[PDB]
Amino acid sequence: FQGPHMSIDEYKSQANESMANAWRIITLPNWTVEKRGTVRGDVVESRKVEGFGKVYRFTGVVNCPARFLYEEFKNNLTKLPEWNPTILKCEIIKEIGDGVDLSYQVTAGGGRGIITPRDFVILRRTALLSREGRVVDDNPHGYISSGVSVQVPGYPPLKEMVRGHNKVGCWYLQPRTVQTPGGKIEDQALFQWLMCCDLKGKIPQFVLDVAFATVMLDYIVHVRKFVAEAKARAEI
């Protein structure tokens, strides 16, 4: 009767567990700087977490409203390949309610040859959060989109591609209002991204630290270009 493959209530439970894990981790103290970016304030940091291993966090400021980026990444996951060349393919498997979905993603190589091309089967939750990490309906402190790797029937590992494993991850956006150098008051986004992938190899931790920092700093270039194009179309 009861088989190896998860139910819909089990997918939602796992999505809620992963979102709470991602929010807990991304708000921990005591991060080590790995790499500062070219644009001012961009940083990749790391730390160790019991049960996950080494986790990486990008922080930077993006020049648009936090709500705008949240609604893009929430509602247009299949458009990722159009503006992010690192994402080769993105398909929604199923949408199951309460901001939970399943997706199939194919990534290009990253970290200058270290991180091979790979595919993923991702369980996501997308929510509005309070400052203490409760789900809210309106007046959010922050906006989250979590991810974790799961197994879905119909999406076995391909012989031609490594099946990657996202242990825990999220994007986490907070609205900021800033005074520019010219004195304009502008609505911007504090953009945070948590990454924690299993790689085979026993590839030295020093090599992985550089490769993961490179992946994160390459991705933010594509986000800023997306935002610049939206501003030039008067969307923001």
Image: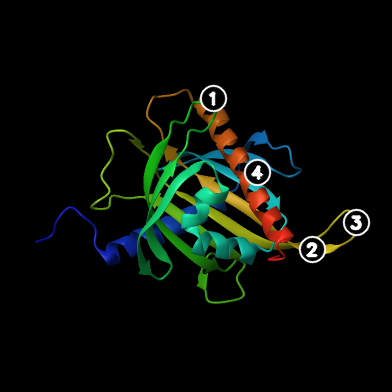
Type of amino acid under label 3: Gly
Number of marks in the image? 4
Q: Which mark is residue 221?
A: 4
Q: Which residue is mark 1?
A: 206
**Residue at 65% over, 34% down:** 35
> Does label 1 or label 4 sit earlier along the sequence?
1
Type of amino acid under label 4: Val
> Does label 1 or label 2 sit earlier along the sequence?
2
Q: Which residue is mark 2?
A: 186
Type of amino acid under label 2: Glu
Q: Secondary structure at mark 3?
A: loop
> Does label 1 or label 3 sit earlier along the sequence?
3
As rendered, which of 180 and 156 lies closer to the eye? 156
Image quarter hosting the C terminus? bottom right
Q: Tell me if label 1 and label 2 are in contact, CB under 8 Å.
A: no
Q: In the figure, residue 1 lies in which quadrant?
A: bottom left
Callout 2 crowding tier (Cα within 10 Å): few <14, some 14–19, many ≥20: few
Res 36 visible: yes
As rendered, which of 115 and 12 lies closer to the eye? 115
Q: Which mark is residue 97?
A: none
**Residue at 40% over, 33% down:** 199
> Does label 4 or label 3 sit earlier along the sequence?
3
